[PDB]
Length: 356
Image (cartoon, rainbow, N blue to C red):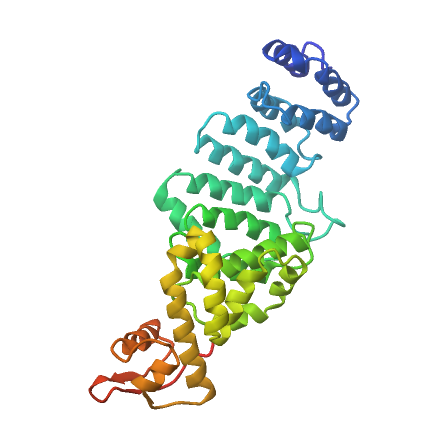
């Protein structure tokens, strides 16, 4: 019987420990547990979880109450109740052992349970709790183990298992916890290309989420110190979603000009949108380089060039003969060609080009 046993003890104690405001809600909690209605009990417990009021009660609740029926209820509902109470502790190692032990219980409590059709379904609960262990690691549990686990989990973002988008999006937070566009934008653009590979029709995302992903990828390319090929980005189907909002149409036309060497359109957007935005202003002198670099690379590719002259490069860049070689020396430094400058003759011996 629940009377004179753990459950009566828990209801009694937690009602005393609780704020008076919580008392009427816990009548439904008591009832639905006694009725064996774990799901209605979870709605009642979710209505408690929805408020910061008395959050620590949920730790005892998890340990001594939810643990009796967590096999039936949704894995993320279960971990959310523990998460709020264990986050209140401001600790990053008990949280590790708790999420690992909880996850491992579900790894043995289930084999064909909570599945779409008693099938080899996605582990669309503990796959995200695995990310929560990783976030907890990256939250300075131990930096060496965290960095090693980050590298191993990055090597696990592949079709080695039937990973859904949600685990990758969850681990993408853990990558963002370690590296950002502020550290390097070319890297963050390539990190964003990972997320594109996982994008498919999923409840996780919308057309608006695609618009935000396209826009953030666009900033990452624009400000990418070593990116040059904006064309493959600008043509990619994900960049069609933003054409159905166009709030940033000026960015995509600045990008378009920067994809074709249209100095006049470039200058016209540069005269306005740079001044309005400090992040873009910090890169203005890179963008004017990027247009010159790409204009020449297109010229080299389309005209299959092997020899060019500083005066003709000066036409194609609007940089004076006295400095124009430093521009193509940046291109050589980007590694997108194997040519060499012949400064003695004010010539260049161009060789090869990276198309993408």
